[PDB]
Length: 49
Length: 49
Image (cartoon, rainbow over all chains, first blue to last red; front, top):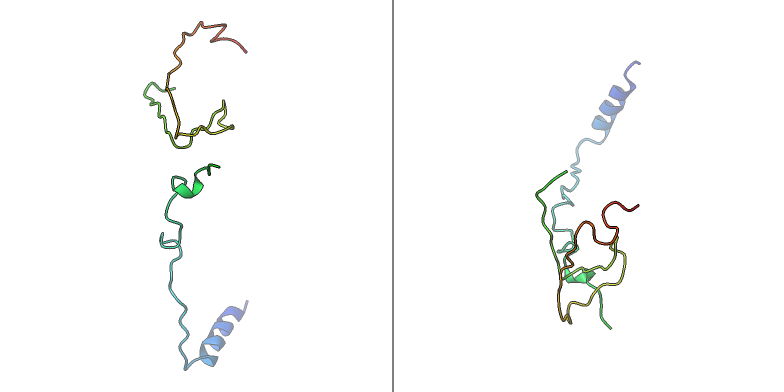
């Protein structure tokens, strides 16, 4: 195998060092990103003429 | 396979059908609510296929 993956990891760590790149940590399933009601909300009720 | 069941009548989402595929009753005008009670032998009832 010769560990091509190890060489790639070491090279990437050495070449980009000296800077900070931190991705955001939002969790998009926390119920703050959903429309409030389920099927029971009046959005899904039939509209009368 | 059970003998502990409940019958729930919800006046929202009243769908008229054998398989609940039909027009929906308007809850805002209802005159009476009569439960249909029959026997097992009512009109070739139980064992027809």
